[PDB]
Image 1: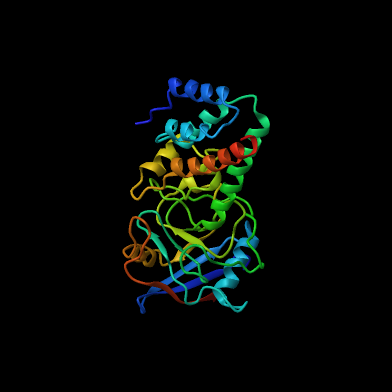
Image 2: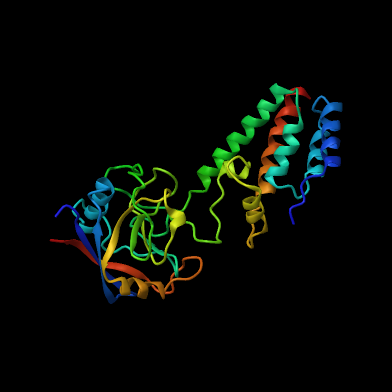
Length: 165
Length: 136
C-alpha cells in the first residue's frame, strides 16, 4: 500500500446521498496526498468530517474542504501554514480528478476540487493528487445541486470520512 | 468596444504637465481627460510624462500602497476559475500590471461591475494630490 485510499460519505441537507472513494497519489505527490489523508481521518483533531461543498459548477467541478469558513476564504493544512505546490506532474485529464483548490501559487491549505470534466487549462496552476476510485455517479449526483456561479441549492456535506485499510 | 485614449487627449495631457509645475489644475484636468479610462489607458497617460522622476516616484509609491491596501481588504476566494467567469481582481490587476485589456473591460463591463478604471483613477488622484502638495 504506497497510495492510500480515502472515502467521503456524502449527505444532502442531512440525507445520505452516497460514498465517494479516492486513490491518493502518494507515489508522486506525497506531501499533498498526506495532507488530504490526515484531514479525511480527523487524526490531527480537525479536518473534513462535517464540512460542505460550498462551490459546485455543473460540467466543471465540485469544490470543498473549507472546514473553517465554509466559503472559499478558509481552510488549513496539516503543516501549520499554507504549503507549496509540490509539482504539476499529474494532469487534469477528465472526470474524477482530485486536485488542490488554491488561491495562487504555493497557497495550499485544505481546499480541493473533484473535476467533472476535462479541465486541461488547470494544468500547472493546481496540484492534482488523486482520483475518484468509487462513486463517480455520486459525484455526478452532487453536480445537480450546483449552478453557474457555484452556489448550491441544498447543503452538500461530508457526513463522514476516513481512510480505507 | 475597445476605444483607446486618443492621441489628441495624450498631447493635451502632456501639454498640461509640461505647462504646469504640477499645480492644482492638473487634477481636474486629469479627471476631465481620463473619462471612462481603463487601467491600460490610465498608464499610457501616465507614462507619456517624462522627466519629472521625483514626482513620478511619489505617484508610483501611492498606487503601490493602494494596491496592497486593496489586496488586504479583498481576500481571494480559493478555487479554479471556470470558463467564462473572471478571476477576482488584485491590486496589480487594478493598476494594469498583472492584467490584460480584455480582462479590464471584462471587469468594467460586468453586471454587477467592478470599476477597475475608476478605482485606479481614485488612487492616481490621491498620488497627484501628494504631488501638488509638495510642489504647490
